[PDB]
Amino acid sequence: STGQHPARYPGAAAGEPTLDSWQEPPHNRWAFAHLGEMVPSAAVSRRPGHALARLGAIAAQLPDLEQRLEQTYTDAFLVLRGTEVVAEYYRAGFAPDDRHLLMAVSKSLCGTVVGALVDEGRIDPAQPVTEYVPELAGSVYDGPSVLQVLDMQISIDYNEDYVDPASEVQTHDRSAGWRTRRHGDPADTYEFLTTLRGDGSTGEFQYCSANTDVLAWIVERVTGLRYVEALSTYLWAKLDADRDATITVDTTGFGFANGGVSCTARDLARVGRMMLDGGVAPGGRVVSEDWVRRVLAGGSHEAMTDKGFTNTFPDGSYTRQWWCTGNERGNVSGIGIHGQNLWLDPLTDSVIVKLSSWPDPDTEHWHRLQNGILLDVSRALDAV
């Protein structure tokens, strides 16, 4: 049993509607207005072929930039300096206002929602996960604090290998609807999370996508809102965004908080703008000044033993669902596999969004190229 979850619509029974019941009353009133949440669906365009490159000023300092973006399978690229869009690129076939999967840049959005609730005093990061989700008793999340979930500092038997069909990654995906279910798989994400175990140790960084979905579960228990709605109420609706974001949902309607958000490059930049504005967005304060300061400050360096990350960023760390480079620029970034970055450059008051589709999820090869671009673009924004 995973306890109370937010109803898909007002008065809905647990788990309703399903793929087999959405045409029946009372579900169908909601379902007929939200069918994409139940059944895969395509856009039928209201609008009746070539890359768009407007690299602006940085083009002179980085003449080969477009080629470098092509080489890293760039779909959308945008640089916001202050409030101004100073460079843009979109591949052939991808429009400026098209949405793109964020993969784990989604986590940084989830952490932001958690931060909003901390500012309201509705979540205390020092409290155990079980203060908010008692049903996680007996699991690896029995004992650790919410902050340890936020900072990915819990040892878990979960192999975050994105190509291994035997990995917990795949089971997580199958439980949530990202892959085809197998017989005997957990019915939904909540159930999957309760199956997770570990040796009990904490304090060392271990990246685990399950952690973010636990955060989303906590958000639901504290607010009574579906995570989809909380993500709107506490973040997206305050951004003055051009378009809605989307998020994949599992069979209970639970949003795939760790990886499933899609949005436009320009709108994602608004999240970075909010961070560089001390937590304030056009629609109001999103998180506290202190929360943003802690993100920029980084997590414990000694917790960060990921050789992959520290080989590039020796003084790097991770906190509150953000990667912190600890470099001389103080760069911090949301990161998602296959080349997604929400990259903050506080020195120049700039945000870099890069949304990509590398053939591979995560290799040293792609990260070297991608980080080289992000750092070169950041430096190109320096006063000279």
Image (cartoon, helix red, strand yellow):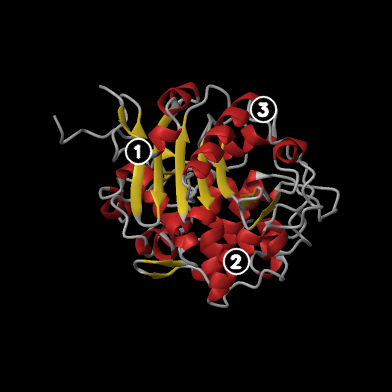
For marks 1 and 2, give the CA distance: 28 Å
Outermost residue to the bottom: 121
Secondary element under disc 2, as helix, strand or loop, is helix
Outermost residue to the left: 48
Q: Are marks 3 and 1 in contact (CB under 8 Å)?
A: no
Amino acid of disc 1: Glu
- Left or right, 159 with respect to 76, comes to right
Residue annotated with mark 2: 293
Amino acid of disc 2: Arg
Badge 2 density bin: few <14, some 14–19, many ≥20, Cα 10 Å? some
Residue annotated with mark 3: 364
Sequence-first disc among 3 and 1: 1
Residue annotated with mark 1: 88
Residue 285 location in percent, x, y?
43, 71
Residue 322 location in percent, x, y?
60, 52
* Quadrant of the image occupied by residue 353: top left
One can see residue 61 in this view: yes
User: Considering depth in this image, is 77 or 124 the residue closer to the camera?
Assistant: 77
For marks 3 and 1, give the CA distance: 26 Å
In front of the other: label 3 or label 1? 1
